[PDB]
Length: 332
Ligand SMILES: [Mg+2]
Ligand SMILES: [Mg+2]
Ligand SMILES: [Mg+2]
Image (cartoon, rainbow, N blue to C red; front, side):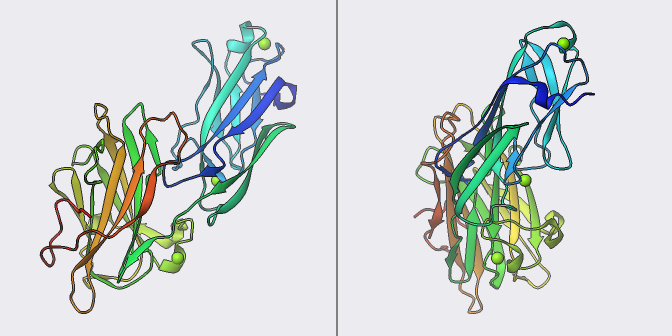
């Protein structure tokens, strides 16, 4: 179990991405590593990759998998994230019989909103031993949309091209206003050829209640101690084609704090369209006027380009036709 980090040779480390990264358009940076393994290495030896706290490796959730390093079709090393957030790779028995091994590794890295608190420049740094790479990038977060007492901010946190999935978060009432009888709907962005498939089989939804608006930062981060899972209290349905509906039904029939809706859905691999979505928050004000406010999220399901050029903005939809009723397709 010798830490041979300093014994690796021909080491290269790099950070690749555009000058601007868009976390809510499934944007991420690519961390790359290259190195030659000394022949003295044996099964059990390890090496450490220094990871900056500003990034979340391989995914936006804690369950993201650390990819193994390969040698031909054999696993060269298996990695794990330690208590410091760094990655520890442990060599397999491949090094016991193979000499002159040269390896590479690329891991997508997402912006960690807990450590990047608002739109601005951030200096990213990663490395192996004394071989480090640095890059300053501009991280962009859009302010939430607000129409009367209805505020909303939708996102697309990441997509998985091979498994045809995507993860989206919708921040309901980030402004902390008073909303009576609120309802959230998620549709395909209208008049577009969206590739999303929204239904009971393809869409998993969880809802969390935030203690207060003050607990939601400009990068939309909420400390785990300030939100709790209330999926049991809302009514989730899919009343129309490719549309989900979340009725909050709180005890007072009013919400005064933000709510986080996490959507894990799927894409139609045979669709030639992009992942285009429109989220709409409905609600009454004190004067019982039923209104609706939307937010559009769109990203190309190409994977080729990191991100950028997508869509992440507010949209005022045609207001509801009937009070208390949602629209099958929120246009305008
Ligand atoms: Mg060896
Ligand atoms: Mg982090
Ligand atoms: Mg706040």
